[PDB]
Image (cartoon, coloured by chain):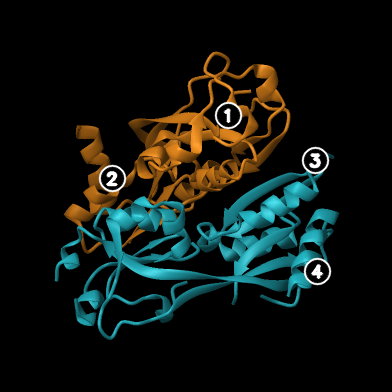
Chain colours: A orange, B cyan
Amino acid sequence: NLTIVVVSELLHTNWTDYVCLLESRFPDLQINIVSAPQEDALQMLLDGSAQLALMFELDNREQFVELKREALIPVISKTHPLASQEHVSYEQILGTRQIVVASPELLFSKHYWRTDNHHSACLMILRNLGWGVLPQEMFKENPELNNKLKALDVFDFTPRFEYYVDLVWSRESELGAAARFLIDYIRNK
Amino acid sequence: LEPNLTIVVVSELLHTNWTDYVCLLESRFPDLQINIVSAPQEDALQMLLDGSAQLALMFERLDNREQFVELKREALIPVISKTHPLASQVSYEQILGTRQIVVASRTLKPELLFSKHYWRTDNHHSACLMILRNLGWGVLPQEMFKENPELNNKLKALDVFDFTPRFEYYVDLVWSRESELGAAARFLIDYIRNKR
């Protein structure tokens, strides 16, 4: 079999092309897609419980290849009181609960809730429990989200929200033919 | 310091309807930090035992160190992409020969496997994506279709003669009976116990 760990922060990005690539050449291969936070993901590469990892931007034992970038959007429920304004201030954002996906660069409110994936974060933002940053991909997969969520205008005092997705693997680990084909295919492209 | 409550939702239950319990807690304890994490059922249990989480959402089927109360049931349905080749022409033997996308916490007993060959994933978003790419059929919570109406445009329920298994989760609220539960977790437990 082939086990790929997609780190929890990247679950709701556009990653399935790489699995379709594997299945097209090796339809008999059993693929296992697991998800865990990044720190756990590296340990799975080292202990061999996963052969490949999809991570966002590593010691001497790992190698990687860059795949793609994924845009993220700060959003709030359209029925949240803050959504009635065309614009918002930093003071207002500071006083609004943020729903943060994590296990300086990402926290901008005094009060926050932590979750480990964007499905959980989205559900809570949809219940008006706060604002947060979600992958643009979620709005492509669920266009009705645009009817319920609105982009929050914080771009003048926040970094560009984005992931740079890498394919990562352990140098010393046994790699079957399928894992090597994907690595070689990506390197060639 | 600062009031906090971590609830672990086991991976298979991530795409069920659980946010009402979070909203009930937030309205009664507005100053409370509520952290929602997900993990395999076995990891969720260890989180209760080592204090990393105070409550767990699990589905029925635990040792004597845990206490639980049943919460609700969630329906799941076997689905396939409307553009899958099989979505034209379907017998049970064809389903046996079509890849299943199995969702299980990251050991598969035969009651979970309905086809000869399968892929494994640890959450229904991942499974749904691969079904959507025509990579197989699989069992998804009905809640996913409520949350994403696009799924009705792209997927359809399997209707196969001689294939009528019933798929449901019975959701339990679980805690460690030797752990310091704060007042907020105790409130939820007492609230559910009264509802019963």
Q: Do labels 3 and 1 share a chain?
A: no
Query: Residue at label 1?
Result: A83
Q: Nearer the viewer, mark 2 or mark 1?
A: 1
Residue A88 figure quarter: top right
**Label number found at residue B31:** 3
**Label number found at residue A18:** 2
Dot 2: element: helix
Host chain of mark 4? B
Looking at the picture, which amino acid does disc 4 mark? Answer: Arg
Host chain of mark 3? B
Query: Residue at label 4?
Result: B177
Q: Are marks 2 and 3 on the same chain?
A: no
Does B169 appear above or below B181?
below
Q: Nearer the viewer, mark 3 or mark 1?
A: 1
Q: Which of marks 3 and 4 is in front?
A: 3
> Measuring 18% from the left and 67% from the top, which residue is drawn there?
B86
Does A167 appear above or below B96?
above
Residue B98 figure quarter: bottom left
> Measuring 67% from the left and 62% from the top, which residue is drawn there?
B56
Q: Where is residue B181 in the image (x, y as percent from the top left)?
A: 82, 58
Comparing B25 with A51, the one in front is B25
Name the image quarter holding the C terminus of chain A: top left
- Mark 4 surroundings within 10 Å by alpha-carbon count, few (fewer than 14), some (14 through 19), many (20 or more): some
